[PDB]
Length: 216
Length: 208
Ligand SMILES: [Cl-]
Image 1 (cartoon, each protein chain N blue to C red):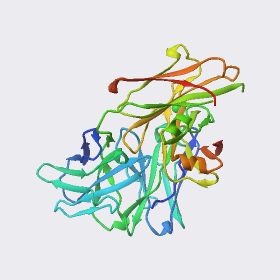
Image 2 (cartoon, rainbow over the protein chains, first blue to last red):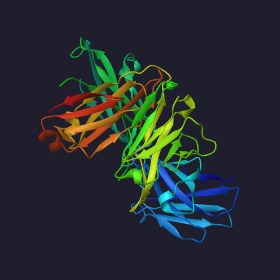
Image 3 (cartoon, protein in one colour):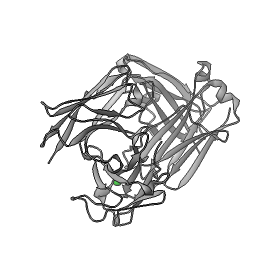
Image 4 (cartoon, rainbow over the protein chains, first blue to last red):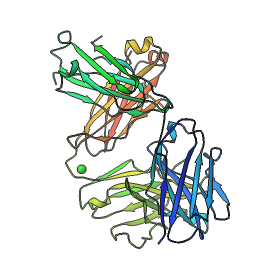
């Protein structure tokens, strides 16, 4: 049986070059095209490129200008270089084997586990915080925009307000920075009465922001 | 370009899951299906339309004709929960993949999402920039589609959407962001967040 396992750096910075390697266990580097693919919510499942042990390559036309696939039969390994990565290149990267034959009947048998690659900001940045103005209830919140890296701690009224607080997981945006929102559901009977202040703590940038949330 | 699959198919244990894959003249090609689980090697569950590799349970069957390839699972088991991708050959890009289908085997009763949509703040607008915030919480299964509308025209730029994440109560949450210029925000009568969960669609709308 032939087994594949990719190795990767985990986290990389935008504009850098991503380098991955697959180690092939069991048989030798013959009879197969050795392929790279990646999976993400935005890219779906997409093929990157493959290589024959003779060095012959074929690439995905949408990725060809940034991609180089190489093989080292002495080490039972093949590799991927992906240049000028941006946050959009965040994905689970797979190595896989492609049997020889007509492309019309070709499919990827044998896959590695996958290696997650996150591409994000090359620098630490503190967030900008904006107010999200509001049955008998209302939702209000705070928008925590453009920070790196995780984590951020959000509390309401220095933590004295806990009921109805829901802080959402961050989105990694295309800029390589994170954004999240914290929202609290409160009685409409409040508003104009009772103050709502979100406290945002981002220790990596030494930043702390307090915002008062009011109805407009 | 891609082959069209439903974003999600949810079944109770034992029900039949049917995943379709649609494309121009797909029936003239051979389709294969990949089962993708997080933390694991993807596996081929079906190749050449209907061939089942050694190792794959008999409950997986495949069909392909016209413009549609269909993966059928019959008596879906919990261990069959995964993302499934259709795949065929393409004359230009060599391989063409389906958009993917999250197959959930229900481990709890369904729950509809609570959706809240926020307009840009005054402060953000004064800093030029503008962000609409759509928060989606307490839904099950953990699969949702979010479409943004400018007035009534679909929005195709500046949408960032998170992968649904499991809350402490075993239900899911997600959020979607629409980035605009201030004039874009002030040019239209309203913006809307359309959240489709399973079959139902709830819409939230805000205006300048
Ligand atoms: Cl569950």
